[PDB]
């Protein structure tokens, strides 16, 4: 059972959540059930993962079996950037909500700040694989999502993969109704996001750390990529506490008051990943881990660098 980070809406976001990207059908259902049994209440989902219907089945089971109540679950999903045009925001959301079998979402995120060609081709690309842009912007999408909050279909809005420039663009938009409660970004010891975390916290925006384990299974992974789990310096700190490298990697975020969403479909690892509240990384250990910062992204999305609101060009 996790502690919480309080949002600006006063809602309580569990500090450890279950990731579901690449969780296969036929395993994600059992994964969600095992997580809930283990005390997970926060589940991180997305339209683009195309598995929300099976996550929904699992949540529903556990609710109808009285394992958990809905008010105690914290469900997050994301709007894919082929759906920034106003009517499409609603249709995509309704599909997400229907798949999850829920009456509301706790948080709804803009998945990426750059708009892609609108429609149900989720990855419009040219011959060379480069993303094809759409003219609708994240501010267009935001306007549409604010309706969902008005209607109570979504308790809070948030963003993902935003730089501080794009968050400023959002916060400084004349006539804003709702503020983002979180910015979900890649974060781990090779990409410590010190500047972006400092910025977000100063604006009352929490940070959710994705790929906390280095996303070691990701398709675009080349052999020369750094491995956090196998990192001797990470393993050293784990050994000190008789814990795993993964437990250290997760606890690292908890101690910066950053929400973290490790993905697994393996019951043993699902349980392991939330056994992070019976030990404490020392100030020196935290300092050591921070020093590992390489500004290395596992998720670069370079195929879209040519579009307007590419977030990773800026320093933070
Ligand atoms: N907003 C975005 O753009 C975005 C981008 C990426 C991810 N996310 C979210 O963040 C979540 C986490 O990121 P991620 O899935 O990219 O990678 P991650 O959580 O860093 O790593 C997941 C991988 O690590 C393995 N693993 C899990 N626990 C382990 C443990 N204790 N020991 C060893 N290996 C372990 C998993 O294997 P098994 O699953 O086979 O156990 C899986 O292959 C995603 O599922 C998704 O919900 C969001
Ligand atoms: O958000 C995540 O969890 C990781 O991101 C993805 C997830 C899924 Cl299920 C699928 C794809 C991505 C993902 O980010 N894929 C890379 C990619 C390639 C081409 C184009 Br036009 C866009 C694009 F984002």
Image (cartoon, rainbow, N blue to C red):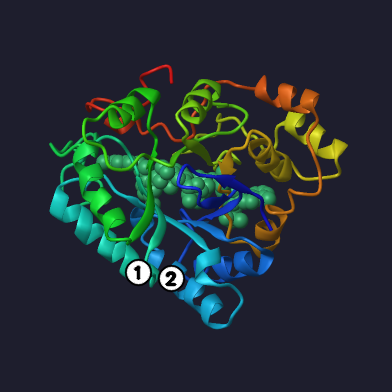
Q: Residue at x 50, y 70 (%)?
A: 70
Indicate the quadrant containing the C terminus: top left, top right, bottom left or bottom right.
top left
Marks 1,2: beta carbons within 8 A: yes
Dot 2: element: helix
Q: Is residue 85 left or right of residue 220?
A: left
Q: Residue at x 57, y 43 (%)?
A: 259
Q: Position of residue 79 (x, y in %)?
A: 30, 50
Which residue is denoted by mark 2 in the rendering?
Answer: 56
Q: Residue at x 18, y 41 (%)?
A: 140
- Whether residue 143 is visible: yes
Pointer 2: residues within 10 angstroms few (<14), some, or many (20+)?
A: many
Residue 12 or residue 186, whichever sits in front? 12
Q: Position of residue 171 (x, y in %)?
A: 32, 30
Q: Position of residue 153 (x, y in %)?
A: 32, 62
Which residue is denoted by mark 1 in the rendering?
Answer: 99
Q: Quadrant of residue 274?
A: bottom right
Pointer 1: residues within 10 angstroms few (<14), some, or many (20+)?
A: some
Report how many numbered discs are placed on residues in the image: 2
Residue 281 or residue 178, whichever sits in front? 178
- Whether residue 124 is visible: no
Indicate the quadrant containing the N terminus: top left, top right, bottom left or bottom right.
bottom right
Q: Is residue 232 left or right of residue 294?
A: right
């Amino acid at each position: 059972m996790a502690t919480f980070v309080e949002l600006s809406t006063k809602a309580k976001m569990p500090i450890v959540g279950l990731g579901t990207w690449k969780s296969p059908l036929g395993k994600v259902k059992e994964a969600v059930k095992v997580a809930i049994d283990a005390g997970y209440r926060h589940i991180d989902c997305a339209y683009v993962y195309q598995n929300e219907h099976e996550v929904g089945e699992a949540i529903q089971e556990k609710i109808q079996e009285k394992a958990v109540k809905r008010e105690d679950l914290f469900i997050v999903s994301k709007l894919w950037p082929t759906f920034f045009e106003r009517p499409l925001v609603r249709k995509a959301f309704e599909k997400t909500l229907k798949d999850l079998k829920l009456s509301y979402l706790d948080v709804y995120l803009i998945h990426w700040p750059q708009g892609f060609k609108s429609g149900d081709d989720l990855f419009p690309r040219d011959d060379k694989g480069n993303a094809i842009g759409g003219k609708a912007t994240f501010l267009d999408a935001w306007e549409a999502m604010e309706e969902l909050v008005d209607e109570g279909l979504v308790k809070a809005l948030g963003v993902s993969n935003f730089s501080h420039f794009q968050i400023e663009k959002l916060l400084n938009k004349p006539g804003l109704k709702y503020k983002p409660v979180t910015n979900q970004v890649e974060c781990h010891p090779y990409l410590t996001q010190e500047k972006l975390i400092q910025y977000c916290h100063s604006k009352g925006i929490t940070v959710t750390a994705y790929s906390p384990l280095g996303s070691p299974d990701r398709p675009w992974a080349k052999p020369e990529d750094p491995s956090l789990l196998e990192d001797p310096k990470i393993k050293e700190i784990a050994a000190k506490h008789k814990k795993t490298a993964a437990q250290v990697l997760i606890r690292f975020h908890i101690q910066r008051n950053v929400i973290v969403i490790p993905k697994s479909v393996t019951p043993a690892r699902i349980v392991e990943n939330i056994q992070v509240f019976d030990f404490k990384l020392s100030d020196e250990e935290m300092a050591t881990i921070l020093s590992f910062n390489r500004n290395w992204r596992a998720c670069n999305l370079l195929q879209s660098s040519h579009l307007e609101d590419y977030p990773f060009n800026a320093e933070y």
